[PDB]
Image (cartoon, rainbow over all chains, first blue to last red; front, side, top):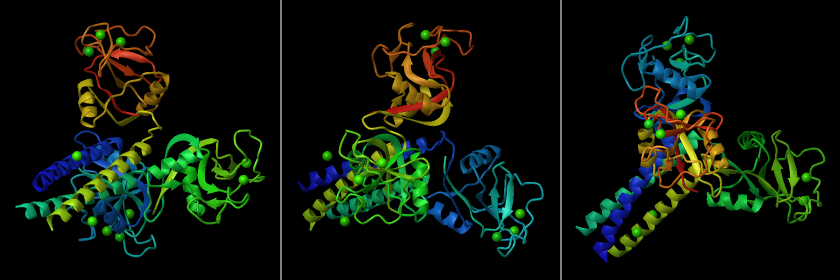
Length: 154
Length: 154
Length: 154
Ligand SMILES: [Ca+2]
Ligand SMILES: [Ca+2]
Ligand SMILES: [Ca+2]
Ligand SMILES: [Ca+2]
Ligand SMILES: [Ca+2]
Ligand SMILES: [Ca+2]
Ligand SMILES: [Ca+2]
Ligand SMILES: [Ca+2]
Ligand SMILES: [Cl-]
Ligand SMILES: [Cl-]
């Protein structure tokens, strides 16, 4: 009994691991993940930047980051409306960095952006960035509520 | 050593349980579940009430129930058409009841509703309720087939 | 106490098996699987036939196969564009077989199809099959890239 039972349970566990792996692969496929390509997902909820970061982290992902023109379109395609990107200049004004560290390698800044505008009325300038429906970027208040779009690896 | 092996397997199972909880959260998210809000989902197949209860209960859910405005809205936006609500007046006509227990509070009936049209010839009167595209409710025979839309806790 | 821990472990694994089954049922439902019907899913990615086969097999599914008009409509609605079907005449030219075995029965060929056309330039004739926007079929090169649509049992 004992050792045989324990050995069986090891196989039961290993089997459940593979089944859950498959379940994850099937769910990623159903949500449009393309082979060897990172994928973006949203629940279409609007919330402040801090909450987006917290939510994506809780899903073991990150706030969507467009690294090139293709991903930028992929993100605008998933969001539909304005969405926060994992890029901010909170650490040093004027210097945008990825939430995952490092300076920008790609940008699609809209005409007259970024400007750290104060007139929004939420207080402070603008330290966060949103991708709008046309794919263009705009620095906005991290306090404002925009669509949460999480990114998961390729 | 048996005990060590056993402890290592307990740790594995705990990892699997966490991974499954994550799988569930990411799925809810991908299907639009909003933070702190009920989760409404549908496959679009229409069937009699008893079947919907059996189906949602198989998924550890309940037939949708719009307890307030936003919820009634969410349901009507996920249903796309006439879908059963978890409400019935089989204990006392006119006295609708949440299948989960409790007297009907919020409501969005249609004019001339409920009429309890006992005359369809398929099974008594109209003891069930369906929400339609316009969000309004109508009392319908529980024998009739309508869209299955389940709800899951916030 | 070894035996108590082993018995709790058995119960833990079963609870996990039960939870994963529910997760799979919920996912299929959210993906549009009707009761007692097989369901079709796509990530909307285009690739050669061998790739689609490999991908669906990895998910424990098979390349979509219409066995009647309803299923043909279901697949057509899911794909939204040209997609490979699990039907080919690669074993014996002119005779179409299902990838899971057996001679093709139900068909929905477009007028003048199949024609084993070589004029595409991809080399060889046309041994695979795509369902197009209107639901009609066309034999095509297995080397061409079409939408990956997988089928999972009822
Ligand atoms: Ca076993
Ligand atoms: Ca700034
Ligand atoms: Ca700005
Ligand atoms: Ca009644
Ligand atoms: Ca009525
Ligand atoms: Ca326990
Ligand atoms: Ca051929
Ligand atoms: Ca052809
Ligand atoms: Cl800010
Ligand atoms: Cl071919």
